[PDB]
Length: 148
Length: 149
Length: 147
Length: 147
Image (cartoon, rainbow over all chains, first blue to last red; front, side, top):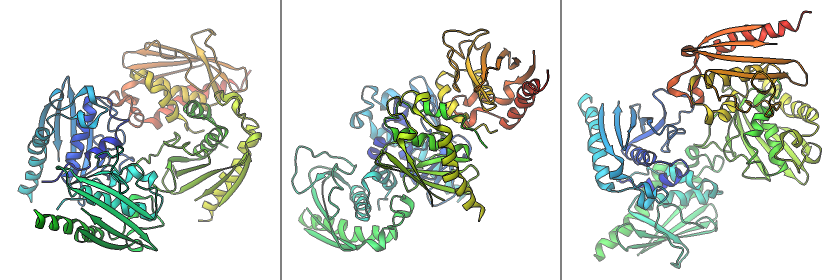
């Protein structure tokens, strides 16, 4: 239901941090999570002093191109998520623990030749949105419904 | 319906440009417009070669603290908006045209002067502000359009 | 008490970004603040998402050569500092709010023709330390005493 | 005598840090610097790259199995030869001024998983400080109080 309105602004905000295909994919994923009601908390599997509840990409989010570990919390709630994006050659393995998983090929969704051009960075973005929603977002929301 | 998800990112993206209460109010207004299906094109009354379709605040948006003139194009196709935010004492008069919805907002009730550049303390009565902008600006434009279509 | 050990490393962590006398003076002041128990938080009057507790100079610290506004927080989080370095002609006025005021003539402390050389950049450094400590550090600490 | 400056030093060193030993030597270097010594260079004897500085000396990490670093007292002539010797998952530290020795398990102080990330690189850092001080720094300082 929700738009991805804000992705262009987020992408521009992360321009100096986006150096590889994985950075661009994680940027997109982050905004999918935010637009579905979550706020970023920080990086790593545990709270640090740098933790801030925010829409922005957490400081240090892009410091490991092989493994992205980002924590989230429901906007006006206490519900928490641990999101991992794991690089495996030209693919990323996405998984979330509140354990939904999803494997994406970077070549299918990111154009490496145009990382500096937002309008040509993402390919098949509508399909990317649906796979992230059905593979990541929806399972989380349904686990929420069952336990009430 | 739509949220204001992205306002925090927008505000951060424009923080150096935000030097007065009016800048902060217009920033808020801009995102209300974008989240309701529009893209920013540019500034002033006149379309020109420096127009660029974007979610970002257009270059020069904050140059006149007395009169903000922003143009928008619907993300889908060629529908258009001309937004004017007019500073009057401690208030701003908003008028929008594609036909002209008019809304007056007291800055004292929506912007904290003391903590201006602090995002989480900049805006007061945000939910009322959203409601009034949607009721006063967004919905009338949409409905007059539906009547015309 | 505390030495200024780390100043050279800090300066080296800034030299490609240091472009004028004021940058070098602010870098020195920053280390006086850090070595006396504070962490750099960010720049400007207001907190932002770019805020980060660090010994390092905050991102954007030298954006404005006329006015440096830096925020600090004590290492335990008990107190905060708003530090302003104001360029006035050949001098800088330093005021810190937790108002401590101190005026430094750049001609007497910074060598403008060797800004890329750490060992020739600073002059009368012992006097500089002493004046910053007695003018800024100590009275800030003692304003914290009376609370 | 704080370890203020360690974060700044680490940032300067991180692009060249590729193993656990690199990170431990960086920490040891700052312990030595903050206790009054400046680095001079590498190897048993002075080389053309010698330079009295707080910074990690040129070529400090060319050999991951054996780190050989020379120091000299700040504003003084007293010299130290520090060796860090890799033995599997441990390092043997000794100082020549002969005088000091200390064995450290890397598993105990360096997180392999988070090496390039400062705040998660060092484990049990307070214990590390105390052992380096008692094992290395103090005997040196005690040496300087006899004969």
